Image (spheres, coloured by chain):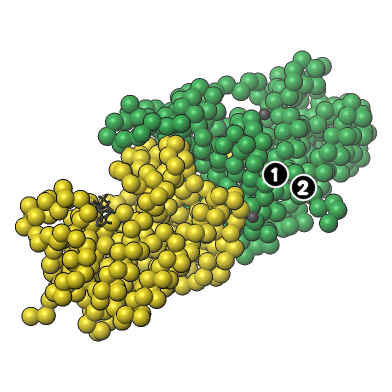
Chain colours: A green, B yellow
Amino acid sequence: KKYQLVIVGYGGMGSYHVTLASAADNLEVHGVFDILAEKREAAAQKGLKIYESYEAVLADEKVDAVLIATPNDSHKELAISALEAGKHVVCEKPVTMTSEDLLAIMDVAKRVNKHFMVHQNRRWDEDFLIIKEMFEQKTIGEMFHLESRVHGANGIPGDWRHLKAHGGGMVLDWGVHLLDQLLFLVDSNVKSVSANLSFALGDEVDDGFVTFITFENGITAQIEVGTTNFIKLPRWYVKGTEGTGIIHDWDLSGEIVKPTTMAPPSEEATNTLSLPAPAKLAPSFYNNFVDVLNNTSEPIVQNEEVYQVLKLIEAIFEAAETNRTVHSIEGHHHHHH
Amino acid sequence: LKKYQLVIVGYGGMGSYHVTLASAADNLEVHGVFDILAEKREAAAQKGLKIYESYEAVLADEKVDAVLIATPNDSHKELAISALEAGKHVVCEKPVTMTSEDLLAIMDVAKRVNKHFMVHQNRRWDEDFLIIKEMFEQKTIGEMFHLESRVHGANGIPGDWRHLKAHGGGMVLDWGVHLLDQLLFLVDSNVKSVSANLSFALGDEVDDGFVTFITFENGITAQIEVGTTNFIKLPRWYVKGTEGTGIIHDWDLSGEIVKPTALAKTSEPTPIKAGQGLTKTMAPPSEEATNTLSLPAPAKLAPSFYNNFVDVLNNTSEPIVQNEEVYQVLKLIEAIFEAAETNRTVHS
Ligand SMILES: NC(=O)c1ccc[n+]([C@@H]2O[C@H](COP(=O)([O-])OP(=O)(O)OC[C@H]3O[C@@H](n4cnc5c(N)ncnc54)[C@H](O)[C@@H]3O)[C@@H](O)[C@H]2O)c1
Ligand SMILES: NC(=O)c1ccc[n+]([C@@H]2O[C@H](COP(=O)([O-])OP(=O)(O)OC[C@H]3O[C@@H](n4cnc5c(N)ncnc54)[C@H](O)[C@@H]3O)[C@@H](O)[C@H]2O)c1
Ligand SMILES: [Cl-]
Ligand SMILES: [Mg+2]
Ligand SMILES: [Mg+2]
């Protein structure tokens, strides 16, 4: 069929999903719901049908799927409601505020036989796909250390991202993208996590963080988000047994430097090269989502992967708060103590 | 004419350079040289320097006031305690000892014999570091709360005895001591916690690099890193404060400072395409929101190490490199090694 999607939450990302979803082959934006009149008015201006309630969205038999782009605390119940009403769900990152909440959603999805997919759009980021190529094709030999940094100097945007109750802060906002990229790329269990949160801005939520992650296969990674950074460190810095790579910024500027376990290095005998062309990740998120609904393809963004990321986020919070190194992503649910 | 006579013990790379360094001081000269190898004793003689046949002979010489110890790390403690007992003041190369307890022993002996022991922490005078010290003290970027200090290169481990655990080899003990000493000299706060990971990417029995994340009791954080397998270098300094950020790229002292203005609060950045999404928060701030400044002139550290050493001997000045500071660094190195070997975060 031509699948019909309703946007639930017509804010900054929700309104951009009209563009994204419409770009897919057999998917259409059918309507919108938002609790704010001004947001509903803006959607009406683009010709979009406005629903009176969320209940009205779910009762509409013409609607095949919903996109949930609300603040982070509402995601879970909205998703569960949708799936219980027979609707497939695309949910904005971070899907839930705890890993146990995703499990519950996955239970519902399995029971009603409807699909739930996290919007992890940044696996398609070109900078990341250049790193993916390098990692897979051994451009700098065995890549054993990765540094992934998103720096800005604008603080925390909007309203709800400042608040703990709405799943605010930068681990949840940007950290989930970079952690999802890391775990998508590296096929290895997490051996250890240490972390520090930034409260430089004096908010009740983190305005940035750093985490040091070691994998079972010996790969180490540093993942960093900052909002108080008036000079930026590079987007990517990666070390391999046969070279080093850098990607400075979103403009994809950078280079590789290679020597002409590791051989004894010398700075006098090196060659500088361009970054390779990005790896392919095909099709787009929304085309893959339609393929998944049609049962023609396996999902690129798997709920099992998303689950591991949430546990990792839970490990990061536990590690920063106790100022300890944690030695698995298991055991941070705090159900029993 | 009241010149202190210094003997160089260990005529290797640094020991031969100490001839030049000690000679530049006002009231101190190089009386001569001892090395355990006859090859190195000949080499010193062929630079017109007096040579001793034994370390015992240096220490028996009434004309000698002080010794400079520039031997591999495992021999520092015995040679220092010997010189002290013989009534000689001591300058010892970094890292002074391989354990913190060893330095406490030397400190005890120096006190008992009423002689001075000083660590050669020469990189406290580094121009790049003194720029950071200027920024830190003058609040150039407001209150500096996070510092990242990195020495990267792709030349591996140099020599020699530095490849071996027995002789206190590896990068923590080589470059780490300089960077950690800089940090602890700058920050007037006790270390609260340390996590660390070592690099063994070259396959040696000692570390070819490390990274550590340090937190102080006053909330200041630091990341210190040395790497010898980095074909691309990250900046020498990257520092963050309540009112700006600074960067020193390299030893050439290139870099800048970027600070917020009072107009940043009422302005809004114009979004860019960042990967698959539009971003406002990670977009450059609007033109009105920031000021870009040159790095300041470096703070003054005066006088030179060796003139300060003489001033300490003449009892006219306190030491710049204090032994208690050197002790806290060695305790930090011990915390780092423990943190990395147990894969834990070490507290105190
Ligand atoms: N994938 C990405 O690159 C990306 C980018 C930006 C935001 N996001 C995610 O998108 C979500 C929303 O982000 P945003 O920046 O658009 O926030 P926003 O504040 O701009 O939009 C949220 C909208 O949801 C509405 N809303 C709140 N509660 C609702 C309810 N229960 N029912 C229906 N509507 C409700 C609000 O009125 C608002 O219009 C968050 O989960 C965020 O993390 C993802
Ligand atoms: N402060 C700095 O910037 C800096 C720079 C380089 C080296 N160093 C330090 O200086 C010391 C020596 O370093 P190097 O690179 O010159 O080493 P090196 O190998 O070049 O020289 C050491 C010399 O000591 C001699 N020696 C060994 N055992 C001896 C003994 N028991 N008695 C007398 N002489 C002995 C050796 O024969 C050799 O000539 C080390 O502690 C190192 O950490 C410091
Ligand atoms: Cl721990
Ligand atoms: Mg996998
Ligand atoms: Mg002090």
Q: Is residue A46 visible?
A: no
Cβ of mark 2 under 8 Å from ligand 3: the answer is no
Chain at numbered mark 1:
A
The residue furthest top is A296
Quote the CA–CA distance across marks 2 and 1: 8 Å
Above or below, A226 relative to A59: below
Verify CB contact (< 8 Å) between mark 2 and mark 1: yes
Q: Residues within 10 Å of mark 1 (few under 14, many from 20)?
A: some
> Mark 1: which secondary structure?
loop
Give the amino acid at mark 2.
Gly
Q: Give the quadrant of ligand 4.
A: top right
Instruction: Residue B22: give x, y in percent of width and height.
Output: 18, 66
| Disc on res. A328 | 1
Give the amino acid at mark 1.
Ser
Cβ of mark 1 under 8 Å from ligand 3: the answer is no
- Please name the residue that numbered disc 2 is placed on: A331
What is the quadrant of residue B233 in the picture? top left
Q: Is residue B248 left or right of residue B216?
A: left
Instruction: Residue A301: give x, y in percent of width and height.
Output: 71, 29
